[PDB]
Image (spheres, rainbow, N blue to C red):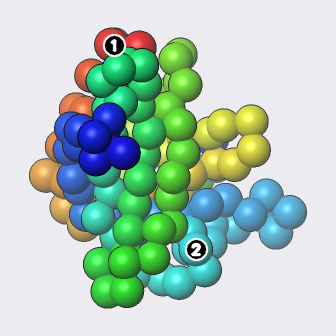
């Protein structure tokens, strides 16, 4: 899961 | 549709999708702003989907099935995310109350599926 913006 | 589906929650969130080619989040539907995001329960099939519409112009920016076994990631108290075989979706909620409402409904759906 990519990091929050 | 209204005949077959009931809303189980509504939450305020900016709906994002991950542009993996460019390694950055982009607004779903191409237009930054907050949407009203529902989880809809199709009671006949016991299926669920996430549907979101911009508050301003009502554009549908998300309409994605919730598959059984989904891993729902609560990265922070106001940003949650999940993925499918195609896309990674993110919800940047307007408040922790909105996040709790949506997460509570998502977790119920995932228990019920």
> Is disc 1 placed on a helix, strand or loop?
helix
Q: Earlier in the sequence, mark 1 or mark 2?
A: 2
Give the x, y percent position of residue B35: 34, 70
In three-dimensional space, the C-alpha distance between marks 1 and 2, rounded to whole angstroms, equals 29 Å
> Is disc 2 placed on a helix, strand or loop?
helix
Residue B6 in view (yes/no): yes
Give the x, y percent position of residue B73: 47, 35
Count the marks: how many?
2
User: The C terminus of chain B appears in which quarter of the rendering?
Assistant: top left
Give the x, y percent position of residue B5: 31, 38
Q: Which residue is mark 2?
A: B29
> Pointer 1 indicates a residue of which chain?
B
Q: Residues within 10 Å of mark 2 (few under 14, many from 20)?
A: some
Tell me: residue B68, above or below residue B105: above
Residue at the spot 53% in from the left edge and 37% down from the top edge: B65
Q: Residues within 10 Å of mark 1 (few under 14, many from 20)?
A: few
Relative depth, front residue between B85 and B7: B7
Image quarter for residue B56? bottom left
Q: Is B45 left, or right, of B99 in this rendering? A: right
Q: Which residue is mark 1?
A: B111
Residue at the spot 41% in from the left edge and 53% down from the top edge: B51
Residue at the spot 28% in from the left edge and 47% down from the top edge: B2
């Amino acid at each position: 899961x990519p990091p929050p913006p | 549709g209204s005949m077959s589906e009931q809303s189980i929650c509504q939450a305020r969130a900016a709906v994002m999708v991950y542009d993996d080619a460019n390694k950055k989040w982009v607004p779903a539907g191409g237009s930054t702003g907050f949407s009203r995001v529902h989880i809809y329960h199709h009671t006949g099939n016991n299926t669920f989907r996430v549907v979101g519409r911009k508050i301003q112009d009502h554009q549908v920016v998300i309409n994605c099935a919730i598959p059984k076994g989904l891993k729902y990631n609560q990265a922070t108290q106001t940003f949650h995310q999940w993925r499918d075989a195609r896309q990674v979706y993110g919800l940047n909620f307007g408040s922790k109350e909105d996040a709790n409402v949506f997460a509570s409904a998502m977790m119920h759906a995932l228990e019920v599926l």
